[PDB]
Length: 129
Ligand SMILES: [Cl-]
Ligand SMILES: [Cl-]
Ligand SMILES: [Cl-]
Image (cartoon, rainbow, N blue to C red):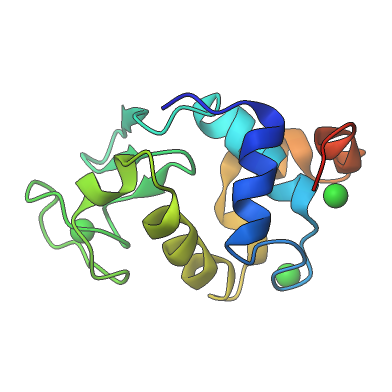
């Protein structure tokens, strides 16, 4: 599924991400736009052989199992394919574990480079939330 901006904002709000660990909703929307262009089916392979999955580009070295990333952990306890669902529940629940790990949203490279320090409230402007 390819979300619209407000539709995704609403779904993230319903699943408890607004101000989760102090990150306002626009941060989460901005990270999804630049990680996946709001496409739940997005995959991208990394140099190390790990792959990133879904709307928040969660990495199989640490967080999920894809059966092809040797020595990797599965800290969210889920197959990586779960992260590609039209239902964002599994992505959200894993993202909450990631953002709790010590480095906050700096775990997401696109957030650090494209969202951090910007007017992220713009990403939710206009939406009925
Ligand atoms: Cl915001
Ligand atoms: Cl893994
Ligand atoms: Cl933080």
